[PDB]
Amino acid sequence: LQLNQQQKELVQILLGAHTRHVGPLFDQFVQFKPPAYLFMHHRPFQPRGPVLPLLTHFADINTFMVQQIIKFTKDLPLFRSLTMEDQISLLKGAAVEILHISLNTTFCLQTENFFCGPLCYKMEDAVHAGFQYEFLESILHFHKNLKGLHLQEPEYVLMAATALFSPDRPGVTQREEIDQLQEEMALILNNHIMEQQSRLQSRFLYAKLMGLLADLRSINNAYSYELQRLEE
Amino acid sequence: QKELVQILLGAHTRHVGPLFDQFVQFKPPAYLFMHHRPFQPRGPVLPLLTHFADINTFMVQQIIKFTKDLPLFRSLTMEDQISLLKGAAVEILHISLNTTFCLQTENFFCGPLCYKMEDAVHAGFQYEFLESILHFHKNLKGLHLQEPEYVLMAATALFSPDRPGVTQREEIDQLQEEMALILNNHIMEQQSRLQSRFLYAKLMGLLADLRSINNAYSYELQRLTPLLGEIC
Ligand SMILES: C[C@]12CC[C@@H](O)C[C@@H]1CC[C@@H]1[C@@H]2CC[C@]2(C)C=CC[C@@H]12
Ligand SMILES: C[C@]12CC[C@@H](O)C[C@@H]1CC[C@@H]1[C@@H]2CC[C@]2(C)C=CC[C@@H]12
């Protein structure tokens, strides 16, 4: 219950990593041939026509986010300290979770749209790309729930690090060493939140976050085929 | 009593709800239709000053139509109605305007329109003033309020007995408290979702920061070339 020098230094390293590779991420989507209507924020009756371009765009931004995210982790000495296998296994399992956690950063609660650069994503756009409604609703509830907590870079990065060092993921060997990492990550998350008692005013913030981390994992386990198909 | 909050709710929804979806009706410069755009202060100003003037008028009219459906209000000396409105109108406008504010992008989404501070800046308004306005809207928005706490907050400001020109600052400093604590109570009747520490105090702390800017800055809210037929 209080952050020591080691911990404060860790937060900074995380933030640094996040800021270089993920923060600038969302503003690069426009480079991946986005369909014209994506540039409009207000389009109640606008048609979308062909799926291919829209579809391959989502394909584009998804690969780019997963790439940057990999870089993100790669900039963490703690992560590098693990075995090749374990890393590939942790990323292979936490990339989607870090993605929506990072993406919530551009999410607007008032309009339930993500503002990435000059682009404006709406749930209906994913619908038009063939994503399952139930999937999309869950993904949406998550983002609404998480935005309502009024988080900031620090809380976002810590949370992401918490999801990264999860041992329960298949293919891991150093299960107990890594589980130690996650616990140190959560304790820093928790204590960090307290340090900001005045800013963060939702009750049971920590639990609510870890709770949402649970919801996220469930959603992927359930509609995993939606993503596996996108990746091909 | 809690039925007075049904009177307020129906008043607001009828004349102030669709208030914002009509701004598109008053010759808004094409750029207000875009959410992502360059700041060009060397651009034409007059057409934008004209717009803000037309919608400032329009808004005032609906806020009048609003208060004109509050029995507790009409049942007062016309010399006070005018007086109270002479200073509340503005304050309400911003409380009601806040429902179109997105905390993420800091824009105001009114119908197909997207208003930015940059716009008030170009219109020629002064920093500090705008700064207060933005600060007000960021703070208030961060409290996750819904209609009930809006119409409510608004009405307690509607009856502010310490306003210049009021006749019976006796029956007014009564009608207000006859709702100030009715606001504090409702806040608890929903203590679950409204979990901001010390809402009320923070709320009234906002009603006070609105008045202070309603004053210090007023000479400019006036300027708003009040000529329509002036163009053919
Ligand atoms: C398509 C994408 C982005 C690429 C891929 O991660 C899958 C997700 C599913 C969920 C999508 C999101 C883009 C932005 C969307 C459209 C907004 C709500 C649902 C969102
Ligand atoms: C112009 C107006 C509306 C009329 C008048 O109350 C002054 C204010 C100042 C502040 C303005 C607002 C319109 C909408 C704006 C442009 C959005 C942010 C700043 C906002």
Image: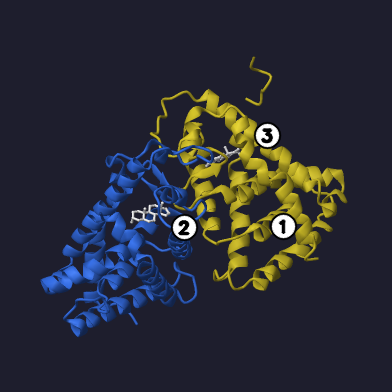
Chain colours: A blue, B yellow
Q: Chain of mark 2?
A: A
Q: Chain of mark 3?
A: B
Q: Nearer the viewer, mark 1 or mark 3?
A: 3
Disc assigned to residue A133: 2
Disc assigned to residue B156: 1
**In front: A226, or A173?**
A226
Asked which secondary structure carries label 2, the reply is helix
Q: Amino acid at mark 3?
A: Thr
Marks 3, 2 in one chain: no
Vertical placement of residue A138 versus A123, above or below: below
Q: Where is residue B169 drawn, in percent x and y?
A: 81, 55
Vertical placement of residue A71 versus A125, above or below: below
Q: Determine the CA span between mark 1 and mark 2.
A: 43 Å
Beta carbon at label 3 within 8 Å of ligand 2 = no
Q: Nearer the viewer, mark 1 or mark 2?
A: 2
| Rendering quarter of residue A197 | bottom left
Asked which secondary structure carries label 3, the reply is helix
Instruction: Quickly name the residue at label 3.
Output: B57
Say whether marks 3 and 2 touch (CB < 8 Å): no
* Relative horizontal placement of residue A65, taking residue A216 as reference (left or right): left
Q: Determine the CA span between mark 3 and mark 2.
A: 43 Å
Asked which secondary structure carries label 1, the reply is helix
Q: Where is residue A9 drawn, in percent x and y?
A: 22, 70
* Relative horizontal placement of residue B33, taking residue A12 as reference (left or right): right
Beta carbon at label 1 within 8 Å of ligand 2 = no
**In this view of the protein, can residue B224 be seen by the observer?**
no
Q: Residue at x 32, y 65 (%)?
A: A97
Q: Where is residue B206 drawn, in percent x and y?
A: 59, 57
Binning the other alpha carbons within 10 Å of mark 1 as few (below 14), some (14 to 19) or many (20 upward) gives: many
Q: Where is residue B117 drawn, in percent x and y?
A: 48, 41
